[PDB]
Length: 115
Length: 116
Length: 116
Length: 115
Ligand SMILES: O=C(O)c1cccc(/C=C/c2ccc(B(O)O)cc2)c1
Ligand SMILES: O=C(O)c1cccc(/C=C/c2ccc(B(O)O)cc2)c1
Image 1 (cartoon, each protein chain N blue to C red):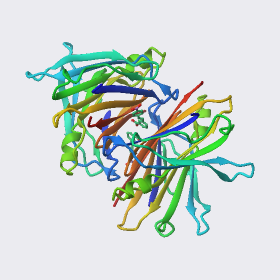
Image 2 (image 1 turned 135 degrees about the vertical axis):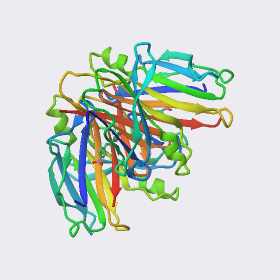
Image 3 (image 1 turned 45 degrees about the vertical axis):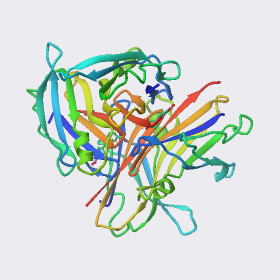
Image 4 (image 1 turned 60 degrees about the vertical axis):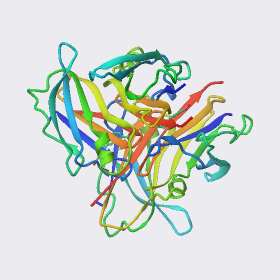
């Protein structure tokens, strides 16, 4: 599991469940090509997106469909989605956790990168 | 204005209005002595808490009454309040803005510290 | 000033100065058209990006160039930039402040939306 | 594990390891009495602080010694510590995760409360 995504709900104090997540890899012509996707689990986590062999160095975008999440709760949100854009860098044998903490008009994201 | 507090609401996308704020300073006997208090304005800002003369070196606690805020709005929040504890002015006088961003089960606080 | 961007530095406890900001608007063909750009001032604020007339209904992307900011400071950050994507003015004109708080491996963004 | 604490470092993108954490329970005279304490692990987590039998309803304070953490990294921080103060409420059979994300001049804390 080189790449894991975790989404939390700051309004209800819970995992953000059944949130759609799309990962893209930046192509040579600067466009975003689909790479992997899924929905967060009951624990707010999305595992199994990719493998060590497939996850090469490059620029990646993680798009979290926050708008649909809030609308399913009857809450009008600000953002269309949350986007996290980063470079994967091999300098070391490591795993990336992209975590996002969601509010209707705000979100915060951090990377936990470990060996 | 050596000490300012600003509070935002992450549910409403607005300033957090009418938030009570209590400031304490640690005394020589290690207890928290009341130092200043007030509430945020329509802009979510609290000015005029203290003066350059009275805001001496020390350890200060800024207590933001988030529970009263959310409850006054009919929401049941997780935290009792948000506490910001810091040493101030120990390299001479600085100006401090304490900012807080509130959600019912989460808050974040940052400080902007400038040299006048 | 219908659109303002403010950026703070959580490592330094200061405004984030000289941060480049690019704004895009989604076009009819679903591509991102350049809309406005600038950089944050000494106060960490970026004013004058647009006007009430030109800031029409649409989907906007505010790209904050956090990597260039941290690298200009000799730090190697995680993110390429911070992107804030939102529908604006679809219930009539509003004023938007987009705030971002930056660390090398983390950022948070909030919006304050007011009705003039 | 009714109560777990997790601490993350936003500067290095890692767990915050070997961070001292003290939990207090508010006593009838409004004073804070020591309840439980420990140091975060290699994963930034502190488990085993208390038990279901001991963790009754009441007001609790979790104090995270952020100052020592940053000083051990040669970074001058703003806060003396991070304090998280909350009421434990039985309305439901649940577990509390108190998470904190640390920067030198800022911190953010969220509660993830689950069954
Ligand atoms: O704490 C966070 O997570 C956070 C995140 C994103 C933005 C902010 C805003 C801070 C702020 C600081 C000072 C002023 B001011 O001097 O008027 C206004 C806003 C705070
Ligand atoms: O963004 C904020 O404001 C914020 C605030 C408080 C905590 C967090 C992080 C939560 C988290 C929990 C577990 C993992 B993990 O699977 O190692 C990672 C992150 C983020």
